[PDB]
Image (cartoon, rainbow, N blue to C red; front, side, top):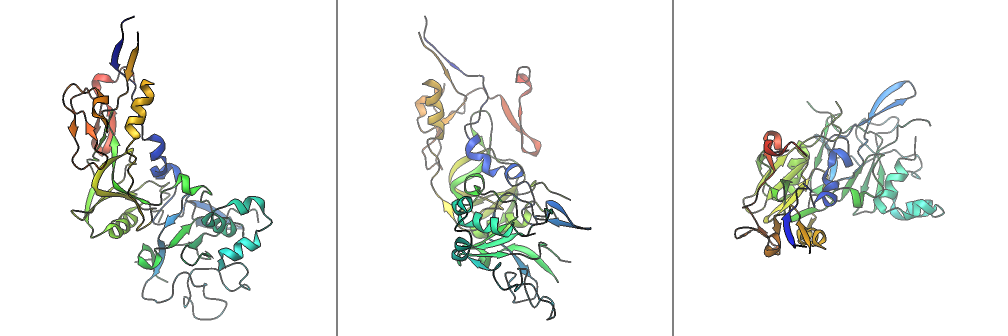
Length: 364
């Protein structure tokens, strides 16, 4: 009979589906700055080759003391060595470079290949050239010129020839593509930076600051994005995508904060933009998913026994059923309120690990 309201003991995270694409270790799973994640036996010899499953936006190779773009064919037969780039040679063109039109005509009678997005079409094309080898060439797609370049050299860094991977304005429309990039990278992989947001850690019902980050000066989002790229998982020893892959850029204080633990939520903060090593150097989506908490609270609700979820933030402050006044979050563009005065069952300990508090370990 008696109608009741209580707080759930289930420890959830409403950000799980949204945040999967930012779990770089799981979704990309190889180096980002330098990706040599797979091994290949080219008949009797031994090679390392890019294996990452996500595209890397804006990445190119910088040839030290040179004016040749790495997108130029490799130096062919005779002719001065590295008077050229990294790309596939001459042949009779026919293979590389190839415009989107050219790729569309080549594969017009392929049903499945015709369904691919442009980046995925370029990727599929490059990875089709060898015969029982997993040695396949990486590609660079130029989104500006709508051109696919197969790369002949798969190495990315030779320093201390001489070259290194970087992100700069000249590479901004380039997408660097291992042979393993997901055809559905638009759903599974980072691209746009997230404005009005910073990365955080979900701690029993609210998204909290990551305590251990490295702070660096950065004038703008592009610089923050370049710095996190320089710091990110490097196979130059297989990283398996583990590294300083993520950064929060404070656009008011002009600081970049890089960290190496996957984020599990976002904090809504109007001063911040959240970026990764894989992400485009400039594109920003400003639309925070404001309804994320309210949707979860309302879904759990819809005499009665109401069990409220462990969600202590929302744009509907009464919905939380906070025992004190919820705090209005000044930096929120969603007008979030937070109930600080509730029992917490998890905490952040060193190395940014979220653990159940000692008091609560038995059960859980």
